[PDB]
Length: 146
Length: 146
Ligand SMILES: CC(=O)SCCNC(=O)CCNC(=O)[C@H](O)C(C)(C)COP(=O)(O)OP(=O)(O)OC[C@H]1O[C@@H](n2cnc3c(N)ncnc32)[C@H](O)[C@@H]1OP(=O)(O)O
Ligand SMILES: CC(=O)SCCNC(=O)CCNC(=O)[C@H](O)C(C)(C)COP(=O)(O)OP(=O)(O)OC[C@H]1O[C@@H](n2cnc3c(N)ncnc32)[C@H](O)[C@@H]1OP(=O)(O)O
Ligand SMILES: NCCc1c[nH]c2ccc(O)cc12
Ligand SMILES: NCCc1c[nH]c2ccc(O)cc12
Image 1 (cartoon, rainbow over the protein chains, first blue to last red):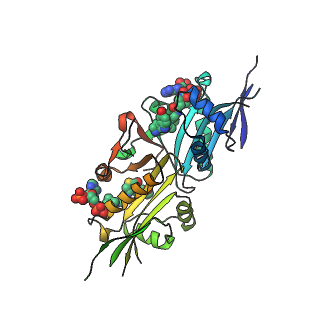
Image 2: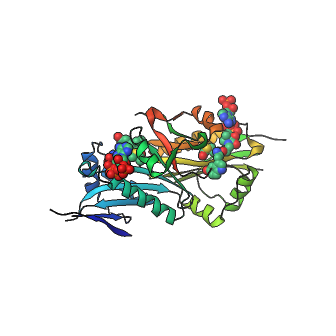
Image 3: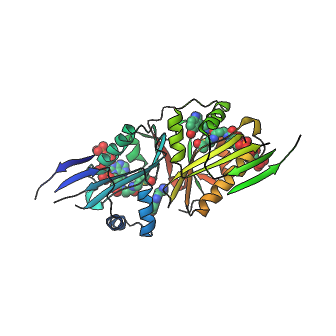
């Protein structure tokens, strides 16, 4: 359940669905992306209670991409926090990470694969096959403060 | 955690967040609403892997309502399969069950409470405080078979 995606020269990219993601490495990444720090114990609790945590590492190991899902292990899953290191965006890695994520969940027989997308990346997911408000279904938040 | 909601005669409604829901009683309720049969092993796996399951019982026990939620135990929950017996709809019980669900989750310190609303009941969740597509964020499904 580990893979080597590509090899370049002057490093590789390794997808994993294991879960060895060090909350300090992840923190480092979220910073690069400008996210605000969250209690590392609470981050560690979210990775532990996530049905699927998928990783891209850049060996020469180095966290350069992550996605994770919750799921009821049976019917539904929801994809959260898929992020890719700025100096690796625009290379196909977000696509590859997502493709394998979906594939992993299909292989575990999750039939309903959902997520919530910012307006600026909705197109990135429609290309991957995601379909917004199908049949007038709406995705709702309790008193969001964004 | 177990509460008595109302008392009537000619019976009391009981809210529980305990989790002990019989998959046979649940399947009975999903037929009463016309849902399709699903592998009891899988139904049972989706309840055990649901961060919160909340039940409505009619004692004189009879399962008359249910809602569950997945969560990463830290940041996000998603509320699925909330349903109440047609014999008991129109009485406030859907509303009561939802309020306590939300309160239980806030209690547990989940800050992001989300769900996916069918068209005919989107209004029902707006009245409870749920806001659709807040500032551009779209709920999305991968190749929905609807
Ligand atoms: C799940 C949620 O709740 S929201 C998701 C959270 N994710 C984030 O916000 C992370 C922030 N964004 C990023 O880190 C990245 O820029 C991503 C993940 C959005 C894109 O990752 P990248 O690696 O740059 O994209 P990738 O290389 O896979 O590009 C894939 C394809 O989508 C297109 N694409 C790339 N970025 C975007 C974008 N921002 N919007 C729309 N399309 C895009 C690319 O052109 C490419 O097209 P093609 O291959 O068909 O020619
Ligand atoms: C979770 C998801 O994925 S989407 C939702 C999934 N659930 C289902 O599809 C099951 C279908 N739902 C039902 O059968 C139930 O009727 C529910 C869940 C919609 C509501 O249960 P009820 O107990 O009948 O609703 P309840 O009696 O609590 O009524 C609460 C309030 O909502 C209103 N309401 C009831 N049904 C609806 C509706 N379809 N749309 C909007 N408002 C509604 C009621 O008028 C009432 O208003 P008021 O108290 O301000 O006068
Ligand atoms: N789900 C709304 C997008 C979103 C989800 N989690 C987030 C965390 C930080 C942030 O800036 C944005 C988000
Ligand atoms: N709002 C009910 C739509 C619906 C129809 N069939 C379903 C099965 C499962 C579920 O979560 C939802 C549905």
